[PDB]
Amino acid sequence: EWLKEDYKNVDRTLALKASDNTPQLRVDFMFNTIAEKPMPLYSTPGLRRI
Amino acid sequence: EWLKEDYKNVDRTLALKASDNTPQLRVDFMFNTIAEKPMPLYSTPGLRRI
Image 1 (cartoon, rainbow over the protein chains, first blue to last red):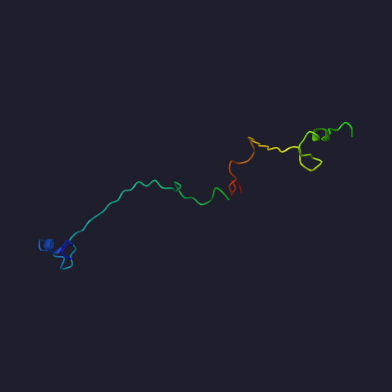
Image 2 (spheres, rainbow over the protein chains, first blue to last red; image 1 turned 90 degrees about the horizontal axis):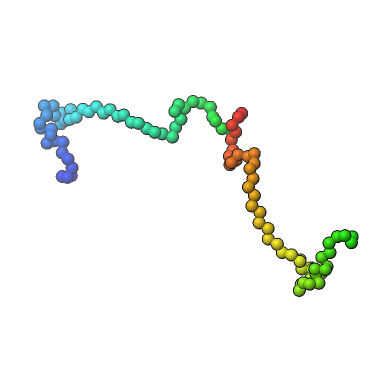
């Protein structure tokens, strides 16, 4: 329990506290992936083999 | 009947006769063929055309 990080030490430096249920952080994440996958370029109905 | 080959002339030279139902010959045949055939390389189920 002692070894875990503590959000209350940062919390006394904030104008709006998390003890007041204001989240300490607001983050925007943008992911860009290039995936080379074992799929056809477009998946169009109809089969090559019967 | 006379013109046919006769196994009995060879047979008197053999330690175990064919008249005793010992075959005169025991042969091992090994065949290696390269066949170029009008078949697909592997025959895998499913058809190209419907």
